[PDB]
Amino acid sequence: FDEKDDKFNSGSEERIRVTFERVEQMSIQIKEVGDRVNYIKRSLQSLDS
Amino acid sequence: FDEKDDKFNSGSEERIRVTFERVEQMSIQIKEVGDRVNYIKRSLQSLDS
């Protein structure tokens, strides 16, 4: 059962699948941070005086 | 027609394709945020006094 994860993990089709699920969630997080960077640049950096 | 998206989605060639389109627009967003982080570090953090 340990060696059974030579196929189900560490295959081409699973590593493509997990990065597809990692990048999909990841792009959402950058879009949130990229809107949060634009929020900090708008609110805080204009109000530095 | 639901099971028809076992092939067109969830194939190796489509999951590679979408991450290719996700990472391409993703790197643009990091380049924008990475220039926006350098902009906040330049303008705001030097003007903290």
Image (spheres, coloured by chain):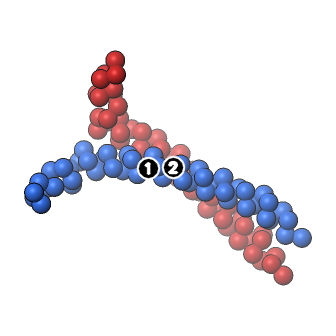
Chain colours: A blue, B red
Regarding residue B26, the answer to whether it shows in the image is no
Taking depth in this image into account, of B32 and A23 the one nearest to the observer is A23
Tell me how far mark 1 sits from mark 2, CA to CA.
6 Å
A34 sits left or right of B18 in the view: right
Q: Position of residue B19 (x, y in %)?
A: 41, 44
Q: Is residue A44 above or below residue A19?
A: below
Q: Residue at x 11, y 54 (%)?
A: A4
Taking depth in this image into account, of B28 and B49 the one nearest to the observer is B49
Indicate the secondary structure of the residue bearing disc 1: helix
Q: Residue at x 79, y 65 (%)?
A: A45
B17 sits left or right of A9 in the view: right
Chain ID of residue with mark 1: A
A48 sits left or right of A38 in the view: right
Taking depth in this image into account, of B33 and B2 the one nearest to the observer is B2
The residue carrying mark 2 is A27
Callouts 1 and 2 close, C-beta under 8 Å: yes
Q: Residue at x 53, y 45 (%)?
A: B25
Chain ID of residue with mark 2: A
The residue carrying mark 1 is A23
Q: Position of residue B4 (x, y in %)?
A: 31, 22
Q: Is residue B43 above or below residue A26?
A: below
Q: Quadrant of the N terminus of chain A?
A: bottom left
Q: Quadrant of the C terminus of chain A?
A: bottom right
The kind of residue tagged 2 is Ser
Q: Position of residue B31 (x, y in %)?
A: 59, 56
Q: Are marks 1 and 2 on the same chain?
A: yes
Mark number displayed over residue A9: none
The kind of residue tagged 1 is Val
Query: Dot 2: few (<14), some (14–19), or many (≥20) neighbours within 10 Å?
Result: some
Q: Residue at x 36, y 50 (%)?
A: A19
